[PDB]
Image (cartoon, rainbow, N blue to C red; front, top):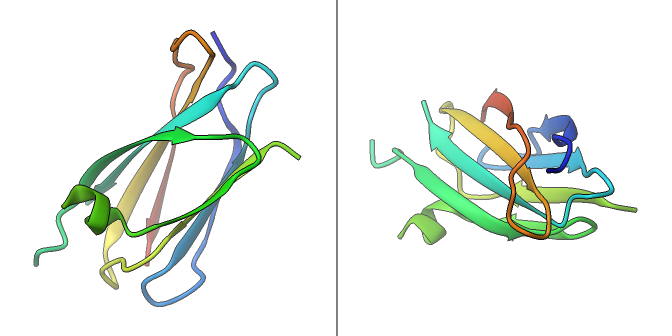
Length: 105
């Protein structure tokens, strides 16, 4: 069972853009991110296979249709609150405890 992700950060890199990043423990093989909104902007996506050392560019509405990890979220609805919850995952599938962050684009 892996340790939770560390230093979960978000940078508002644009009107419709947000860059998430975090550090992975040494037993972390991959990460799961549950991304939700808080008017077709309603969103609930479960993104799997996020790997340590890899940067991703993701349009979450498309999918809905070192050893850090970076996720650039694009096409977000401006002025909307979003919640990202990241779960670390060991090789066998066991999940660490979640770490969550809320941001408004």
